[PDB]
Image (cartoon, coloured by chain):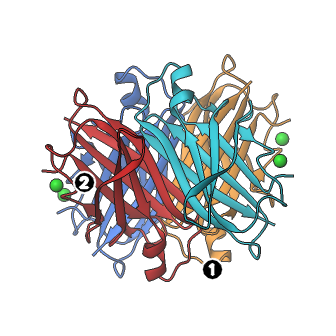
Chain colours: A cyan, B red, C orange, D blue
Amino acid sequence: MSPLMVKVLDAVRGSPAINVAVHVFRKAADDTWEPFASGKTSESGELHGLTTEEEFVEGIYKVEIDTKSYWKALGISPFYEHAEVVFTANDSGPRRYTIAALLSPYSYSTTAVVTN
Amino acid sequence: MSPLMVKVLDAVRGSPAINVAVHVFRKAADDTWEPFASGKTSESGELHGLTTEEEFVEGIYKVEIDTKSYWKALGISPFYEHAEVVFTANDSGPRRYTIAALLSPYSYSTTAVVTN
Amino acid sequence: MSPLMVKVLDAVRGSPAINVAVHVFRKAADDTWEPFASGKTSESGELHGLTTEEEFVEGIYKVEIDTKSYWKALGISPFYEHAEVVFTANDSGPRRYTIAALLSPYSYSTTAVVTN
Amino acid sequence: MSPLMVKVLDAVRGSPAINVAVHVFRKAADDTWEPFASGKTSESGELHGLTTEEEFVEGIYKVEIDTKSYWKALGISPFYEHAEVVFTANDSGPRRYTIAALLSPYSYSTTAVVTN
Ligand SMILES: [Cl-]
Ligand SMILES: [Cl-]
Ligand SMILES: [Cl-]
Ligand SMILES: [Cl-]
């Protein structure tokens, strides 16, 4: 249902990154970042149900992944604490966006898979 | 001289990412992001002279790399427009931080190399 | 069914990497690389049915992804032509391995997700 | 002097990957991989002096990085044991190749920077 999905992996332990906090913001008319959607990744490392086609309108979006809470519960104090990426949602473009991310204490990688 | 350095690479063309705008922010007491330092990468993809040991105090820092202006001048309209990473500078930790980044239209990777 | 799965993504076009040739080798007693399994990624970028629990015994495995044929059909002549990674399968370890890969003309990234 | 350089980083500890064994092979006329050059990364994570312009002729090259010996001495038993990438050296192309790599126990990333 959700045209925005987030999937997070762990490069140190070779696993889905479970219980990772993900926050999505949408740029408002005044150019502030408005809270749009948020959630936590499941046991699969996937975060479903973030939003819907009705709510996910055209706009500039920021996807933030908080790595601090995640690493600490696994006994790690990371260097990279959060990572954020910004993109524009455009109705002419294909309709499902998957933001994949890979976490390590000193490294962050993300790739967008845009389908349909 | 600068205890913070940024180096940016291009995954599509296999080159240093030249003339990439980099902005650094430092979290203020009120928890807003204060502009701390900024610059553009050289022909080597490296950004030197960002700050000094005197100015780079302990704190939470955000490093933002704007990919839009970079890709457009190379004739590309990217999906990922900006990428940001947050870390804490701590005086007890080693004293030089190098933030390396790799750019592609739909992908972003960064790693911190912390030495001395 | 397959305890080994391969998933491939495209960093330039932001998509599953479809029709990517994947070859798996297993190190033999004489220390040569014996052809073990191979296939092509589906429209999802995923390669299923590579092997079975009966055939996927303990051993040293190499997973090779050929990027040349893939990029050319998309009109690209890449610099990185193939990428290979080696790991040991061990029965005591968890039983499903997913090798994820991200492709660009001058860059290659892979991460293993080992579950169950 | 060397038109081929290799630089290796560590994503777990946020450092240059020091004393990493790097092996380069060149495809022979019979299509076997002939040992071409090898070395170990310095304290900077860089491997200089691999070859020379006279020896580095046109051909298909494989760059292998052995991660097992590296991780073990740091007290880690990695999943990814080696990673290899293949490219063609072509005299018409620019003349310096830098192969950068990023290591983690379950992840490997590499990018080529081709200059001059
Ligand atoms: Cl969903
Ligand atoms: Cl400097
Ligand atoms: Cl399957
Ligand atoms: Cl040299």
Q: Residue at x 49, y 28 (%)?
A: D78
One can see residue D61 in this view: no
Q: Which amino acid type is marked by label 2?
A: Leu
Q: Is residue A44 left or right of residue B109?
A: right
Q: State which chain disc 2 sits on.
A: D
One can see residue D105 in this view: yes
Would you identify the image quadrant in which residue B20 lies? bottom left
- The x, y position of residue A74, in whole percent, is 55, 21
Label 2: which residue?
D50
Q: Which amino acid type is marked by label 1?
A: Gly
Q: Is residue B112 left or right of residue A15?
A: left
Q: Is residue B93 left or right of residue C103?
A: left
Q: From this view, report whether residue C11 is shown above or below residue D63.
A: below
Q: State which chain disc 1 sits on.
A: C
Camera-nearest residue between B63 and C25: B63
Q: Residue at x 46, y 52 (%)?
A: B84
Badge 2 marks a residue whose secondary structure is loop
Q: Residue at x 33, y 71 (%)?
A: B18
- The x, y position of residue C97, in whole percent, is 69, 34
Label 2 vs label 1: CA separation? 33 Å
* Within-10-Å neighbours for mark 1: few <14, some 14–19, many 20+: few
For the image shown, how many numbered marks are present on the structure? 2
Badge 1 marks a residue whose secondary structure is loop
Label 1: which residue?
C75
Camera-nearest residue between C16 and A22: A22
Q: Nearer the viewer, mark 2 or mark 1?
A: 1
**Label 2 C-beta lies within 8 Å of the nearest ligand 4 atom:** yes
Camera-nearest residue between C32 and A37: A37
Q: Residue furthest top?
A: C92
